[PDB]
Image (cartoon, rainbow over all chains, first blue to last red; front, side, top):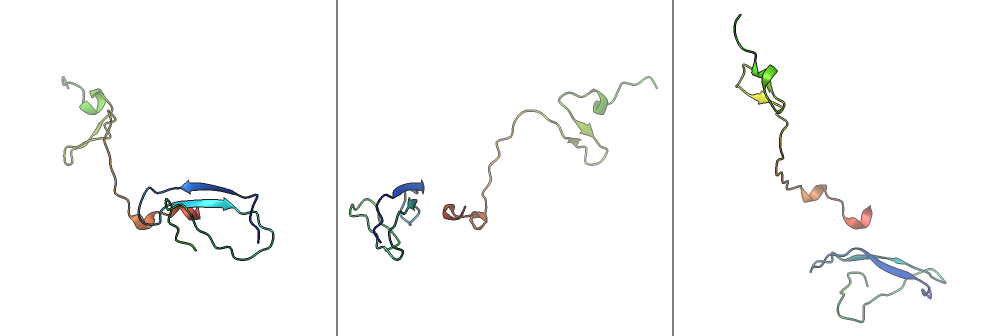
Length: 49
Length: 49
């Protein structure tokens, strides 16, 4: 699925080591299925691939 | 019969009395710096509310 026309926002970001940072994402898909994710910036490390 | 009145009838700042451990119950005055360590198990993680 193409996911654009979305929105992302943190909801409780934890300024920390353990994966405490969270963020809802208003996904706006075309199909329905899986969608691999990553932050190309090294600022954020994500638990979910 | 020529006494004075009782401290549970003349005290200030709101107290009651007992001939018991000599407490002065329920004295409403000032503030108390209270601090608690909650059980972390009782917390709900942020991504569930």
